[PDB]
Image (cartoon, rainbow, N blue to C red):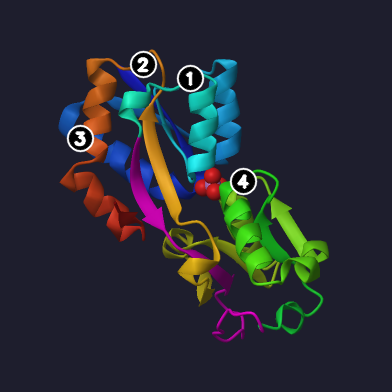
Amino acid sequence: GKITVFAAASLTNAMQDIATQFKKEKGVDVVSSFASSSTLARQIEAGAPADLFISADQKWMDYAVDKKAIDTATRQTLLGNSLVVVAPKASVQKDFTIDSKTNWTSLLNGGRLAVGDPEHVPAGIYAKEALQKLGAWDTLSPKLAPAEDVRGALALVERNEAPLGIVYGSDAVASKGVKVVATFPEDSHKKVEYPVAVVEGHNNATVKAFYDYLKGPQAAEIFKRYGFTIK
Ligand code: MOO
């Protein structure tokens, strides 16, 4: 048959490699749809036919669970990640530490801070939480360059349309055109976690085979290579 995976945008590269490998060794076609975790959860709620859902936060998985769209016994935290600040590869921007007294205004210099839309994209929600805890939010809000998902934010920095952008550590590994210039302290935000679950009514042997593969060694190898931490 064919499996349909709805996965957070930050999983783009890893999921494509995993799908390729699974087809080589098991013969099944895996089709992935990538977007903000919020967008995917709402599509699943509406009735879009996804078999698996992997969210970049617990919030949007909880959302789908409440709408009775998830086979709950299958829900499990699969990956972890870090929150970082990236700059264009060829930028002269130097490394910096992030604390209560970081001078964001000087760092930006009339430029905007690329972020996933803090209204709903997990990467933006983690970022807003961190910036509010570090007291930088009030200063930064009028200087944001929001995007549809974390990869949209990444693109803004790669195309040098924003001096800095807040993305996941894994995004930096996948990107050929940016560099990590700072890392948020773990205590500034909720732990970045990626729950996976089978969509209600799609728990059959074919989907289950893929779900099990995601927790196996071949997949763990690919996830690690892309900067994700395995839970
Ligand atoms: O759902 Mo994302 O990976 O925070 O854009």
In the picture shown, does residue 124 fall above or below 164? above
* Part of the protein shown in magenta: 76-101
Q: Is residue 192 left or right of residue 102?
A: left
Measured Cα–Cα span from mark 4 to mark 2: 25 Å
Label 2 sits on a secondary structure element that is loop
In depth, the one of 119 and 107 nearer the eye is 119
9 or 92, which lies in front?
9
Q: CA distance from mark 1 to mark 4?
A: 20 Å
Examine the rendered structure and indicate whether residue 6 appears above or below residue 133: above
Q: Upstream in the sequence, badge 1 or badge 4?
A: 1
**Residue beneath disc 2:** 202
Q: Position of residue 185 (x, y in %)?
A: 50, 72
Camera-near label (2 vs 3) is: 2
Dot 3 surroundings within 10 Å: few (below 14), some, or many (20 or more)? few
Q: Which of the two labelled residues, at mark 3 and mark 4, occupies the earlier sequence position?
A: 3
User: Residue 28 in the image: x percent, y percent?
Assistant: 25, 24
- Quadrant showing the N terminus: top left
Residue placed most toward the observer, 130 or 147: 130
Of discs 1 and 3, which sits in the foreground? 1
133 or 120: nearer the eye? Answer: 133
